[PDB]
Each structure stands twice: as structure tokens, then as C-alpha cells.
Image (cartoon, coloured by chain):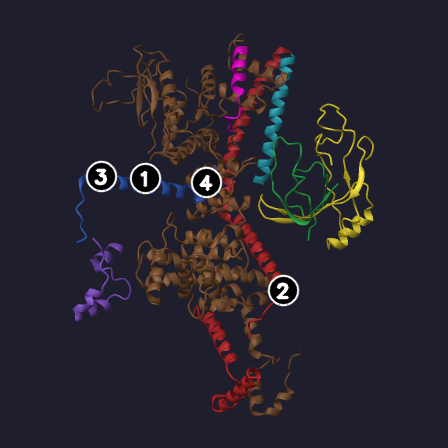
Amino acid sequence: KSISNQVWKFQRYQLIMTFHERPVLPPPLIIFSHMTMIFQHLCCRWRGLKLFITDDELKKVHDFEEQCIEEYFREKDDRFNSSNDERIRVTSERVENMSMRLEEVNEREHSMKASLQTVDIRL
Amino acid sequence: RVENMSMRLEEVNEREHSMKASLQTVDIRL
Amino acid sequence: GLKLFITDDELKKVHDFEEQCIEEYFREKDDRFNSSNDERIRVTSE
Amino acid sequence: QNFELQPKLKQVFGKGLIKAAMTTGAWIFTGGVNTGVIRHVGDALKDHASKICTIGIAPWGIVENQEDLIGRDVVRPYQTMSNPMSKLTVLNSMHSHFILADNGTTGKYGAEVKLRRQLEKHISLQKINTRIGQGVPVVALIVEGGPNVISIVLEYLRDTPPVPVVVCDGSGRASDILAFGHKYSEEGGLINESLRDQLLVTIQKTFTYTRTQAQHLFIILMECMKKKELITVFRMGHQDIDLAILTALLKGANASAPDQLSLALAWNRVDIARSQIFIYGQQWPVGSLEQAMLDALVLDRVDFVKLLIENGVSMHRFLTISRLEELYNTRHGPSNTLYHLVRDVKKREYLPPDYRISLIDIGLVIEYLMGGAYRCNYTRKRFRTLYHNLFEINHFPFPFHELMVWAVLMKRQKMALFFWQHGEEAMAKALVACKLCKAMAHEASENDMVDDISQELNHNSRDFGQLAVELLDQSYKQDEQLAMKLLTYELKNWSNATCLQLAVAAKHRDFIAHTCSQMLLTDMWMGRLRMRKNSGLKVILGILLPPSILSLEFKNK
Amino acid sequence: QMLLTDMWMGRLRMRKNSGLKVILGILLPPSILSLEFKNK
Amino acid sequence: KICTIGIAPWGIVENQEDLIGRDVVRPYQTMSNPMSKLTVLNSMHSHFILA
Amino acid sequence: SWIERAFYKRECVHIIPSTKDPHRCCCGRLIGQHVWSISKHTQLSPTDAFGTIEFQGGGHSNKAMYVRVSFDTKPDLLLHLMTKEWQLELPKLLISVHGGL
């Protein structure tokens, strides 16, 4: 029941291609359609879902496919970069850098406050 | 906002380095 | 049938392999705990 | 003397040191007595905690508990009894080896420096087994240090061979002065007057040297800076010191760039090759990039293949029949199930262990796994006469197609994904890869191989089929008619089939459940009729009553 | 499971469609000579 | 699409001999010497004009 | 062939002044590599360097056409060339990117 519709559409392709391959007339009258097939083959010899694209049409089909690959990979990258786990990871790594840089800023500000006190003492 | 924090705190660090250099030069002048 | 009798040196490298597996297992468990979302939110909030 | 550092600076210094040591199998010549940068090395190996030699060169007279170290071939007790007021210093407790330099005295330094330098040089004159550079190579890491650090920097740079020196700044003392000079040195002695005066006054005051010897240490520094091509800096601000160590490794080697890329392939560090090896001015010989491409492909190094393609190999020109045949017969990579499949195929058509797997046999393997009426382009008559007459008429028009097939057959999944991204006819490649991966999964499961092999091959199909489904979704959202044309066009490179038939052979029910294939099937189902509502009943009334056909809605031309 | 499979087939390298070949080996003792045995 | 028509001088470009050729798809790599006065062009501009 | 018969090319044949380094002329080229007219004595020759560039290295391969144009040419020939010989439609914007060299 979870695979029902997918199996049904696969069987749809199977029976559609099969009945496209069949002759026009039913089996009890298929002798007539077989004779028309033989007569058409004798006229041509002794005297469905497969379109054949031209070169330029194939070129723009390939260009369209390459565009679809590029936007698919860009969309996958954007979904990875907007996933919650990646966001928490990059936030935590930048917070690591914050603690490091703010401790350095605090030490530099302590040194600058000592220098300002010494400059005020000199004045 | 954390993006903006990293940008603004890097700018603050560069400005504080310039201010520390200016304070050292002012102490040398005194 | 499924009970091979290892020699002394083979047993020594079997024990060394087992100790390596314990060490990488505990390191992997620590890395999975440190990359869990709850621990990340905890350390970010602290 | 003992100093302090930034915490994560020490952490990434330890991680870079440990990573470089594990990648190169290095011997570490740390001082050994637990004061200063040696204490940072002990914290570095605590991060590793898992070979790696750490041969210390420490003086014998300054060690603590000298009576404990007496004893011939005896496992002596040596505890971590470190008195805070004693002049003697205990050794580092997890160094792998030790050397006690005995000059006869006690509590005096300088008994180990000359022996350590002569032992480093004696190591450097030993010819290595690979011989990629010039014997066994040495790098010199420097953190802090006094004037003796500058003296041994001058001794290292003027040495024959000229061993490179990596300095790590952010620590103060001589290393920060060296890095601040090297930032503004240009051609060594090309330093402006204000920067030179600032360096001299920080030498005299910030590190409290004498001002009379400041000019002497300045011209010693200039003699160091005359060989600036080997001095390498590390600026922290991920990006560990292992990048520096290795760049120093392939910087001082006097080695050619093919051997440099071979060493980078051996270490699997793509970033070192990106930074240093693929640089401007590097004269690659004829076919050296193609040979490095072949070595990267057989070793399953997808990132080096990406880097090489980004630098230009001309993928069309590299892939020949012989190159792909050597690619199929390689064994310097992950294990595959190819040999069993060629054995089964050659048994069914009708094996020595030295069998050269031909491209024809590979093509019959594609015919067996693909199934049905798929005729591989290898087993066609034109390629057979090309193979008979040769074992750009040996190159391939679509090299990424055969590289996709090569990667799928030899279980290189990441390389197959990369080769899926690059090239044309992507959905056909995805569906063919899905069918091939499921077919080797079935062949492995039927012959009862390792269950992990069959499970991972299924997973590979499932991934390739999922790629085909998402590509179909993207093409359907962009342009519907072009998605029709992409689904139902003849693929000359894939045995004149369509994407629908390739999905059908792969039993890909997710592919034909999608709206695009259903529109194509509905459009070919009704044919030239535009019969829209309550069809079937009107079909029956058309069949039974032929005048009812004249009242039907037919489409235009 | 690899250990159990390896001790299950013993010295035989019988790989595809085993069991049927075991039955034909038991009923026809000349069929054993056409079986794939592993090396030492 | 997006044109990126560059207006760069011909005499300052690197590998001037590579740019010679009538209606020929010439090789132009990213050989940028750090000491050369000539500067290589940008490698993904859609068009170019050499003054 | 119409591209070479429309615009112009400039070649440096001159007295080769010494200036600072005598190998470099006023045009800055090598003293033997020769072959505005003020101090450079140029002659207006037909154009020769036009076509397509294959960009290998630095990521993806990109094709970029190029036409060597003299600096003293008419802009209507360039405009007709850009609209006809390059098949580029007229834009709705001209984003100049002037800045520091």
C-alpha cells in the first residue's frame, strides 16, 4: 500500500508501450492486419516515444541539462547551508573566535588603560 | 546577527590596534 | 571449529588492536557528544 | 624558560604538529626537559593520546633524580617528582625516546646543542628510501626563543643543505620579531628606516636586550633575511601549523614538481598542493600532469582529480583506450567485484590470475548487468576492429561517460558522483549507474559475497536513482517541453535507448511516477484523440458505432 | 556471519546456488570432482 | 546573458604573442608572474577589447 | 574578414630614445623587438589580432572573443561590430566599474 501508485504507474508504462506495439486489429481479425503489414513491407522492400532530435536541438537539450545540474547543485548547497545543524556549527565556531578575540581585546584595553594612566601621570 | 558581530568586532579590533599605536606615539611624544 | 588457539605474540597484537578500538570508540563517542545539538547550545549559551 | 600562550593557539599548534607527525611518520626533536616549548609539546601529545618518535635531546646534568637513571638495561622508576624550588627539571613523561647529553657537569646548559645539530645534519645526509627530495628532510619549528634562536636560525639557513625554518608568531620573543620583520622585509634588507628603528627599539626594550648588541643582532637578522625563501611564517586566523610544516617540507627539498605532486598524493593533503605545488612558474614536463592524473585516478583521490581538472588536463585528450584499460586493471585502490564479474561473463561466453581485463570484456560485463537488449558500445563491431587494429581514433568523444562506467564498476562512489557532475547526458548516466549498481548488488547477493558489499551497492543505486529523480524534478520545474524532449530522445551513447527505457530496466518506480513521464504516457495513450472527459466509454461507443467517431474531438496537426 | 558462513561451507568454495550442488554431490559422487575447492 | 565586456590596453597584457591569430581559438592560461609588469586578464569575462 | 578591414592597428617604429634604460624605448618595448606619432612615430596598419580565447585553468573553461581596436577609431564601427558580428543584443543597462588600478 505504500508502493501502490508507483507500481501502478510502472505497469502503466509497460502496458502502454505493449499496446502501442500491437497491430490495429484484434487477434481474431489479426490475419488481415498481418496481411496488410506483409503487403506494405512487400511494397516498400522489393520496389512512439522516441523522438529523433536534430543537432542544434540536441545542443540546446544538453545546455538545458547542464543548467539543471547547476541549479540542482546550487539548491542542494543552499539547503545544506540553511540546515539547522550547519547553522549551529558555524555559529559555535564563530563564537569560539569571539571568545578568543574578545579576550585579546580585553588584554589590549587593559594595556591601553595603563598607558593612558601613565600619560595622565606624565601630564 | 552573529555574522554582523564578527564583522563589527573585527573592525573594532583593527580600530583598537590603530588607537593603541596612536597612544604609544602620544606617549613617545610626551 | 571456530576456536583458534593464538600464539603469544599474536595474542599481544590482538590485545593491542583491541586497546586501539577502545580508544577510537571513546574518542568517537566524545566527538559525537561534543557535536550534539544540546551540548552546542549549552556551550554557546554559557 | 617557561612561557604561556593563547589556549587555542596552543591547541591548533598541537593538532597541526600531531597531524603532520602522523602524515609523515616524523621524529620530533623536542628539547625534553619540561620547561617552555617542551611543555607545549607534552600538551600536544596529550591531544593525540594514541609510530611517532619524540626523541628528546636533553642534558644529563640538569635532569632530576640522576641516581634513578643509573642502571644497565634496567626498567628504572622515574616519577613526576618536580620540586618547585629545585634547579633540576624533570623530563617530559610521555616522550617516546630520550638522549642524555653528558659533558660531565651538572645544571649547565649548552651540553646538547652541538650534538643535536650534528645529529640533525647526519640524519639529513642519509639518503631516504623514496629519494623524492635530498635525503631525509628536516624542518625547524620555532616558538619564542632568545638570541640563540636567531643564531640557530642563521645556522639552519646557511647550512648545506639549507634546511627550512618555520616560525610561529603570536608568541613574542624572537619569533614575533622575525615575523614582523619578514612581513616588511621585501628583498631581505629592503626595510624602511622607521620600521628598522621600531624593530631595534622593540629589541632593546620590549624583549629587554642590550642596546649595544641590538645592532649586532640586527645585522645577524639581516644575514638570516638574506635567505628569506626558506623562512616560512604562520598567521593564525582550521588553518593549523601542519600546512606550514608540509609547505616547508616540499619547499626545502630541491625536488621537481611531479615528485612534489606524488608526495602530495601520498599524504592526501590537497590544500598543500593547491597552495604551493600548483603555482605560477612551475614547469610541468610533457605528460607529467596526465601521469599525475592517472595516479590520482587509480588511487581514488577525487579532490586531486578536481584540482588537476581545475588546472587543466584536457579530459578528452588524456583518456585513451590503453589509459582506460590500465585504469580497469589497476589494484592500487579500493577493492571491487570486477574480477568475479569478468570470470562469470567469460565462463558464460565460452581464468588465469594474470588476466588483462580488456575493454571488450568490460563491455560484455555492461551487457550482462544492464540486461535485456542493451548492446554496449565496446562490443560493437567498429570498436572491436579498432581494438584489434591497435592491440584521434583512440580517444573518446564523451570521456565522462566511460569514466562514470569505470567508477561505478569499481565501486568508487565519490569519483562516480564527481564524474556525474561533469559532462553531458547526466540523467542517462544516473539511470545507467542506478541499474549497474543494483545489478552488481544482485550479483553479489546471489553469489553470497560480503553483505556490506551488496548493501553498499544497493545504497549506491538508491543514491543514483535519487539523483535522477531530483534532476527530473528540476528539469520539470524549469521547462516542461524541454523536459519532454530530455526524457524521450534517442541516446546514441547508451545503445539507442531513451531515459524512460533506462528507468524501466532499472525498475525505477520513483522515476516513472513523476508528472513528466505520466504526461508523456497519457499523450501517447490517447494518440491523436483529444478525448478529455469520460474517455473509455466514448472509445467503446466509437468501436461499436463507427458513425460516433465523427462526433469526436480530434487534435490539430 | 562471515565466520559462520566460512565454517558452514568448510573447505568448499561453493559460491552461487549452493545446496543444490551439495545435493548433486551427495547423490552423485562423481559430481564432487567438478566442484570448486579452496586452496590451502 | 550577462556581458562583461572589458576595456583593457593591449600593450599591458601578458602573453601578447598568444593573442595573435585570425579567427583562431588561442590558448590563454593564467600564467601570472609575480614580478612581471604585464598583467594577465580576468579569466571568466565574457568579452574583451584590446586598446 | 570585415573585422580586419574596419578597425586599425598601431605598430611602434621610432628613433628608440634611451631615456633611463636604453633597451626600453618611449613605448617601453625591447630595443630589437620593434617591427600616436608624437615621440613614437606610429603608422596605421590593418588589424591582425581578433578571434576567440580558450581560458584553461582557474576553474571552468570560458570562451571570450577579442578584437584588437586602435584607440583612435570611430565608435559606430565598434557598435555595429558588437551588435552584428558578436550577436549581442542591446542592454538595458551599462554598469561601468571604474575604480582603482
* Magenta range: D214-234
Residue situated in front as seen by the camera: D173 or D111: D111
For the colour cyan, the matching chain is B
For the colour blue, the matching chain is C
Chain G colour is yellow
- State the residue position of label 3: C12
- State the residue position of label 2: A57
Amino acid type indicated by mark 3: Lys
Foreground mark, 3 or 1? 3
- Dot 3 falls on a residue whose secondary structure is helix
Amino acid type indicated by mark 4: Arg
Foreground mark, 1 or 4? 1
- State the residue position of label 4: C42
For the colour red, the matching chain is A
Chain D colour is brown
| Between discs 1 and 4, the one toward the N terminus | 1
Q: Position of residue D423 (x, y in %)?
A: 54, 55
- State the residue position of label 1: C23
D278 to D488, vertically: above or below:
above
Say which residue appears at 43% left-offset and 70% top-offset. Answer: D372
- Dot 1 falls on a residue whose secondary structure is helix
* Chain letter of the residue beneath label 3 in the structure image: C
